Amino acid sequence: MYTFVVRDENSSVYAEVSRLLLATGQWKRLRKDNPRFNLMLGERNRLPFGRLGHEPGLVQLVNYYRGADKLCRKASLVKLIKTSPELSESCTWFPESYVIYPTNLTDEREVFLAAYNRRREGREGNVWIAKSSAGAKGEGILISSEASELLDFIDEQGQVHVIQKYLEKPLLLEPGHRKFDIRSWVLVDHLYNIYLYREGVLRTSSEPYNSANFQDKTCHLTNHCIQKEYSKNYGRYEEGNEMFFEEFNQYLMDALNTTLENSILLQIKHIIRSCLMCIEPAISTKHLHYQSFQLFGFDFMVDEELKVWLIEVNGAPACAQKLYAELCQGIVDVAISSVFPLAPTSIFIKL
Amino acid sequence: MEVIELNKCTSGQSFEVILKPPSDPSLEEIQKKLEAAEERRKYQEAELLKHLAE
Amino acid sequence: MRECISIHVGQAGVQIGNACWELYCLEHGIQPDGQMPSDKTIGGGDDSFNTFFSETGAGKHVPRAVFVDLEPTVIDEVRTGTYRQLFHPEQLITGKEDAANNYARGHYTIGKEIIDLVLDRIRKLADQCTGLQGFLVFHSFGGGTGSGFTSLLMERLSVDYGKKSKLEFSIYPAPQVSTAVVEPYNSILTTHTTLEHSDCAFMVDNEAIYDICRRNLDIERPTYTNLNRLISQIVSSITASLRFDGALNVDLTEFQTNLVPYPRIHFPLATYAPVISAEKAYHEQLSVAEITNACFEPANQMVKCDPRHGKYMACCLLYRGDVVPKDVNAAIATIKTKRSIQFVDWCPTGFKVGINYQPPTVVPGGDLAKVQRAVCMLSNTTAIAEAWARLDHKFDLMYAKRAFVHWYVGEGMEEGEFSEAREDMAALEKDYEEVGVDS
Amino acid sequence: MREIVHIQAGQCGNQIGAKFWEVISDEHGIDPTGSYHGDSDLQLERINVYYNEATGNKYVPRAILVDLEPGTMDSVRSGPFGQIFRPDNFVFGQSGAGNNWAKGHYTEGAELVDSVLDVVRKESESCDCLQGFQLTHSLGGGTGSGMGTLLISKIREEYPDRIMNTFSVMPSPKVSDTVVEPYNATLSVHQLVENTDETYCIDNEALYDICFRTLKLTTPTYGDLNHLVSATMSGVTTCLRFPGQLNADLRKLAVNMVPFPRLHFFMPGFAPLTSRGSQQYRALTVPELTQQMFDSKNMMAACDPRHGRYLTVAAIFRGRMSMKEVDEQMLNVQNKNSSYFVEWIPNNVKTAVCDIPPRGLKMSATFIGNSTAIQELFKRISEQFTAMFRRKAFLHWYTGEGMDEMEFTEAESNMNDLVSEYQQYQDA
Ligand SMILES: CC[C@H](/C=C(/C)[C@@H]1C[C@@H](OC)C[C@H](O)C(C)(C)[C@@]2(O)O[C@@H](C[C@@H](OC)[C@H](O)C(=O)O1)C[C@@H](OC)[C@H]2O)CO
Ligand SMILES: C/C(=C\c1csc(C)n1)[C@@H]1C[C@@H]2O[C@@H]2CCC[C@H](C)[C@H](O)[C@@H](C)C(=O)C(C)(C)[C@@H](O)CC(=O)O1
Ligand SMILES: Nc1nc2c(ncn2[C@@H]2O[C@H](COP(=O)(O)OP(=O)(O)OP(=O)(O)O)[C@@H](O)[C@H]2O)c(=O)[nH]1
Ligand SMILES: Nc1nc2c(ncn2[C@@H]2O[C@H](COP(=O)(O)OP(=O)(O)O)[C@@H](O)[C@H]2O)c(=O)[nH]1
Ligand SMILES: [Ca+2]
Ligand SMILES: [Ca+2]
Ligand SMILES: [Ca+2]
Ligand SMILES: [Mg+2]
Ligand SMILES: [Mg+2]
């Protein structure tokens, strides 16, 4: 009989994973501070990694990679891409971004203003965005072209923000004239095998894209929470603004002649591989005293030329409603049972 | 890969390799603490003997 | 020549001390008798080994060491053992009853009664020093004596010898060989009161040594003897620079200078290689590059932690045996491209290297194989704070219910000292976190 | 931390005490005349803990024999090893205590107590460094219960900084002499909660159940019961009598076992225990010792440890075996049943190994548990006490000795507080 502890109740994914474990009958759930566990489903912040792997007679595993936050923090991701001898600025799939510390509490201000003299007289669209390392659930973003409107919006809040180059030409979905982001889920096991979930999702805008109306960013930065609020046309096509891969493939064959497999997913597998292999030697638990696995949520943005761009990497993602059972079962199958056996074929693609 | 300060002798040698540059309480206080603790022990024992005498 | 006095406190300090002085004698060719044939200067000298050994007119080489324990049975063995002629009775000090795994009993109750004798015997050794540089103190964290009496001793030493350096070799508690439930209490209590009095402390986690003995020496259930022979090899590597001709870590002050930028952050991580079983018949001898790369393996560390998730402040490589600087530089160059070695911004990314040509000496009939080259890395990394975190958590679990606390208050300690010691530890974890992490 | 002074009081105290000395004398190679005749120096290394040295290489138990009637101690002189005890250490009256705590504690016992303390003092003065005291007695009679606890209080007055340890036999209707046993036991427990550091709760109910259910003995005698106690007392004192790292003296044992001063009542156990008879020469294994020693049906205090949690545990293995296997076995018991050990005391199970096995066994294991389930023992005594007290039945035997009802009310209140304090940590 194996044992585990739950130290993050707010996890919808691992509440389901936990429920799955108990229903196997070969797993027992313990108190959160019982150190005699095989598996830790840990908290989202200040996870006590230093306390793992110090229990004689116990193989221990945790559902997070220590240091994986360098991909998951908005401000840390930019820093890592720029200063890596594997990524560097030889990164053609990530929007130009600059880290902006406020002028009260190092920084790339005269790098955002120094590189700004490129589209000012360059007569190119100078649209930028403003995201927080941890915004108010789904709010705290200001999109504008005025360079002096954003270098003071960050000095209006009490944290560090990242100013990211906005894709003025996003790929349009019809009928609707809308802008969407793609979510793919990635599972990295203890052996550091990269497992992409075959089923991704599309977070669609429930309102026509508007290049004019800028202060109303409700058809921009579509998130399945704010969108439901402001949208007075909530899901005329699909439930909960969720378009799935089988259907998106059909729209691609109808209105763009090509398919999903042809190039877009190709650029996606390259992106996931590039980020995770970059961080491999730093976070791998190859010969550590404890083991790690983690579920990642990569958010993508495609454009008119079917080019894939990278928004964020979510370290603690929630899944789509219809995929929960399948994905969570998959997590148990390759991440947990592979370490703790019992007594086909899988739904993943080993990158 | 700068090697500096190489020093050699019959017993061996030493050097430095740089990959990249940068970018109280008195004796009396102690006596006071030890004596205070001793006093607390004495008081606790006194209370015990008092309880036993009852 | 500047002398060093070694102080061994409690069972762990004494038994480790035994192992170290045995190994010292082997390394310097000193008989249990105390005679040293190779030494042509009779009854005195200013050689490098004289830093640890004084001399009598009859040619006996006497360890500059004091053994202290609150009960007599462990020191008794030294008195009646192989190296009994090495020491004279004044150097071996014993009480009647021990501290019963109680810091308060070792520090306040029993410590108060024996502290003045201990200091006097130490003063006698110091009186025979033309230039005492300081002290090396050996003790466990978990024992009543090793924790309680040591911290009292350290306070008085700071008073009696304000200018002198004080280095620690400390045994961090591990359940697989631990003898008391209250060891986290004793560990935190002693670290708090010792902190401002220690210049550099080398923590050895019993768990790490235990696992190394199982993993690499194929010992099913390691004993204290097995553990201490490995520990003494580490200690010897660290103190070799003080006992032999050389230019690196040549005095106690240099340890602080080279490894301890910030006073409170004075706990260097030791990592040693290679550890090879004396039973293995056909063994292939590891290269400079291999033993050096092994220094960055958590499995070879004296404290299990992950340096990848921390920052270096300093790094010293101490080699013994067939080693030339060219091969060290080649090894470091390769390792730097394949390892996560990040220094803090206000420190040079560099390595201080020392090489002693004499290969490690092993105890005949021991568990360790004779090797041609070995290395001990001393790195000040913030990752060692993992050990403080583990210890502080165990403290919190028990203290929240005040478990066992009455044992300490019964000895005259105040409950507030628990909280005061725990807060200092919380500040210490905070200090490490600032140095090693960026927001 | 060297010498322990042993005191045995009353019939039960002297009977179990006599057997204890028989068993350990055999283990240490001491013959009934006090002469050493062993083949190992392991036997003599810590012999001074329980034995004084006389002239002619004679070893004499540091033991004091106390009773208010001469009968049982006459039996001790006549029994095996009767000659080994110091003749001047026999202290006895003629009146008896009639199974009455008051008589033992306040009247008859009070007259005899000073002469006992004279012998204790004589033994203590001869000690290089006295650890403390151990007392064997029952709680259900008059001498062991009443005078035993009187002695403990007097000794604590003269030696406030020494460890006091008892082997206390708890009464049970299953093996009962008089109806007033719950009175005597409740009164004694109140003394024990205040004046002992460690108390091994030896429940005659559990001993009987073990003899019946486990050992298949139809009609268990005191001889049977005492063999269980004798073996357990040998095991629990192993760490004191032989060279070792863990719980090597009384104070270190207490510091490891007692997280709160009142909660110092231990649940002992022994293994192997096997009925006849395809199981006497059979090779015993480490896993078999470990599983039995932790089994609820094997505890020597009639309570169910599965209903409670362990604050602390001491385990002692004896004989030649694999320490690697001992470690693995102790680990899996904890890892597979972690809920039964409080998480707020990390690593609360401690293991000791001694090379010398007990007589007639190649290997054995002794269990010592501080479990919150021990409340069931005190709760049982409390119910029996209350059943009589609510009607003031049999009280006249006590009030006739100068006691009043208020003292009974206090003892009852104190024992019920003990029960609830054990309950507090069972849910903490
Ligand atoms: C851990 C402390 C400890 C608590 C428990 C629960 C412990 C654990 C284990 O023993 C150490 C059990 C053990 O490993 C077994 C499973 C082989 C087994 O012996 O369990 C019992 C029943 C069990 O209680 C249910 C037992 O009475 C008991 O006390 O178990 C049936 C028996 O049928 C053949 C067999 O199946 C109390 O000190
Ligand atoms: C010999 C014994 C166990 C054993 C040896 S080999 C094996 C597989 N089990 C234990 C000995 C333990 O010291 C305790 C003795 C307890 C004696 C009994 C209470 C009683 O006096 C006696 C009549 C017995 O019941 C047996 C003789 C059957 C006794 O062996 C039972 C027992 O487990 O003894
Ligand atoms: N490595 C090693 N650790 C030891 C040795 N002896 C004891 N320990 C460890 O030290 C801790 C106990 O401290 P001790 O030194 O034995 O106790 P003490 O300093 O004598 O203090 P008291 O006996 O309570 O008066 C436990 O964690 C043991 O695992 C030893 O010889 N080698
Ligand atoms: N286990 C055991 N219990 C005993 C023995 N003799 C008496 N008892 C128990 O002790 C209680 C009676 O106390 P006892 O010692 O006979 O009275 P005392 O002489 O005044 O101390 C009853 O609960 C008996 O069951 C014995 O030899 N072994
Ligand atoms: Ca000389
Ligand atoms: Ca009379
Ligand atoms: Ca008198
Ligand atoms: Mg000791
Ligand atoms: Mg009787």
Image (cartoon, helix red, strand yellow):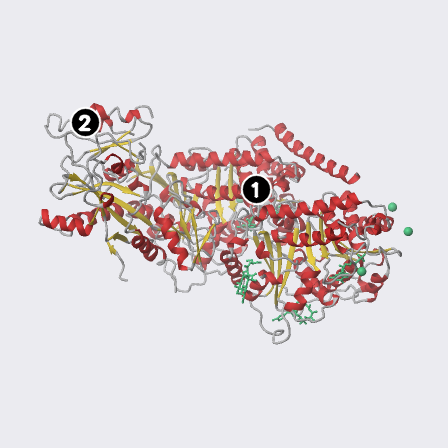
Q: For mark 2, does the 10 Å Cα neighbourhood hold few (<14), some (14 to 19), or many (20 or more) residues? A: few
- Number of marks in the rendered image: 2
Identity, as a three-letter code, of the amino acid under mark 2: Ala
Residue C122 found in image quarter: top right
Numbered circle sitting on residue D5: none
Viewer-closest of C271 and A25: A25
Chain ID at mark 2: A
Give the SS element for disc 1.
Answer: loop
Residue C323 seen in the figure: no
| Image quarter of the C terminus of chain C | top left
Which residue is disc 1 drawn over?
C401
Q: CA distance from mark 1 to mark 2?
A: 59 Å
Identity, as a three-letter code, of the amino acid under mark 1: Lys
Q: Position of residue C384 (x, y in %)?
A: 43, 42
Residue D409 found in image quarter: top right
From what the image shows, is residue D17 above or below residue C1?
Answer: below
Which residue is disc 2 drawn over?
A114
Residue D220 seen in the figure: yes
Mark nearest the camera among 1 and 2 is: 1
Is residue D285 shown left or right of residue C237? right
